[PDB]
Length: 93
Image (tube, rainbow, N blue to C red; front, top):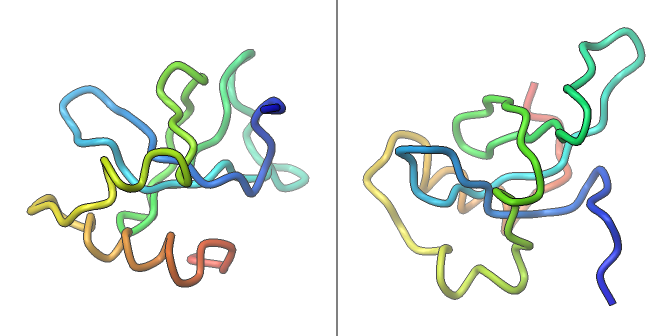
């Protein structure tokens, strides 16, 4: 059975106006800005941008990849598909 989301989990994350996007739940480094309550720090692969999202916008990657894991014209998307499949836990800083 599912647990709550934790750092390192792989997802497609949904933002208004964007396709479901390959991403991970990030850690929050000591001294780093914390998300709002009930929000997670989401790192989006390919763009390497961060937003704060709650679970309603988070789709576990294994369950969802057949639906959402297809190329897209949007900037950074296809790079992001490579990253989530091939090195999802690397430093992209």
